[PDB]
Amino acid sequence: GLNGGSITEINAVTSIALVTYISWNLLKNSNLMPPGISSVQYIIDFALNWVALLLSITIYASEPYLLNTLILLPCLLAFIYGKFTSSIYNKKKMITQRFQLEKKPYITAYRGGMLILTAIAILAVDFPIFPRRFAKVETWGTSLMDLGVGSFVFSNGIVSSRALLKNLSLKSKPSFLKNAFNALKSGGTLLFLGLLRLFFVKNLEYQEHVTEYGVHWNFFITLSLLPLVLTFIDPVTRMVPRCSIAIFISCIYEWLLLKDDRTLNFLILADRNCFFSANREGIFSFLGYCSIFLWGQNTGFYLLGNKPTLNNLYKPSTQDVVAASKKSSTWDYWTSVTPLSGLCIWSTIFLVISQLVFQYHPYSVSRRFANLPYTLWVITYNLLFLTGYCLTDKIFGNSSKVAECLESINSNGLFLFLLANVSTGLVNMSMVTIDSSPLKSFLVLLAYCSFIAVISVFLYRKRIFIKL
Ligand SMILES: Nc1ncccc1-c1cc(Cc2ccc(COc3ccccn3)cc2)no1
Image 1: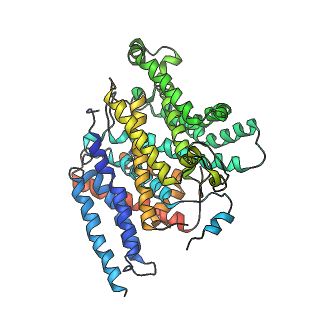
Image 2: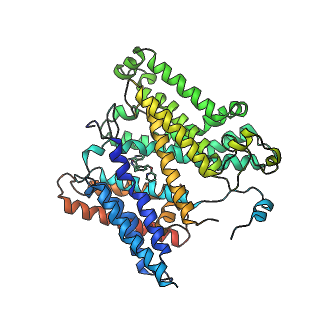
Image 3: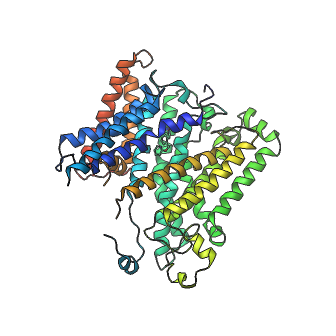
């Protein structure tokens, strides 16, 4: 585990995604780049999106800051050059238009960057050029490979918020059993893949990873099982908002963990004799994952809309606020917000709460147990990133297509993820990784990235979408 590393290094390493996005937008608006599409656009996109992240993670991990400047300062200059070679929105349209869901570019960029980072890190973990401080921690610590799950849960909750809103828009309430069947149909593929991976592990008899998730439990099972519990709870969430339920669950879990020490002693040093004693880690982390999913849904609630609505800060509503504005009170005026102000409010509240909790916590963070500080840290980081991406989108003024690679990876995330896993397995069976000198490993990584990018672009261009 090597105890991991500090958070500030993690933020400095990850900011490269946002820096590259800003540089790409500047290059697009610089007007020098020729109008028709050609090899130049593809080369520039590949260099900006894939090569920069790989350079940040492995070779230039020691000095990230300098790298960022070398990405931003040149492009900006080119921008100005365009501005020297060269010597609408309607309120009535908003009033007349009803409530519909609208896709946003920054969400696509966010998901594409997340998926690319993961795909790179999965293969990069084996080679020696990858720094050892970024490896996953054993019991207590912070590392770059602990934020991958939290981010995924947050994004899935944000996405499911749109299904919630669309269901609410319908005039007839669907039956509860129909909702359960829809959840089962959604989770069937993940459950089937989990069982297949379990059987493949039986056949492999590979190395033990018991402390990670237990004898039988796995990430796919939890991902498939979350929605069923959410639909079971939704009846209660009708009477009180989701945020209060998440707070209550987290408080109960933390009190149970902290009131005494025998619970920790049993959770850490117990024998594996019966089934419950065999898979304790996954069962106990399920509560934290549920809390993260709930907060992600609540955050996406007002983000995924197209126009401001009444009390969209914590509740799904489709009505209009201007009619209320004739005699709007203080509460109705404060709570009904546009996406940016709501993001800012939640960000500040979570920052202050996280600072207090980190100040007065006796233990450290832990991924195995998914205690309170871990969830707080994940939520605060994700909120900050999302606010940055929204601010960039707003200042650049584009509203109402992001780079090609981001859209291509976003379209077929699951299939490309499985293909990436298969390719990493094959390349590991190909050669001995720990032997390779740095240049050879870098060349191998470059070839693998090129192959994946070519496959993704070819799949997207022919308009073929595969769902597994
Ligand atoms: N190894 C894994 N296994 C299973 C699951 C996941 C992972 C995993 C993937 C990563 C790469 C990574 C993704 C997301 C983020 C934070 O989110 C954003 C959003 C926008 C821009 C930049 N980052 C950091 C780092 N690290 O770990």
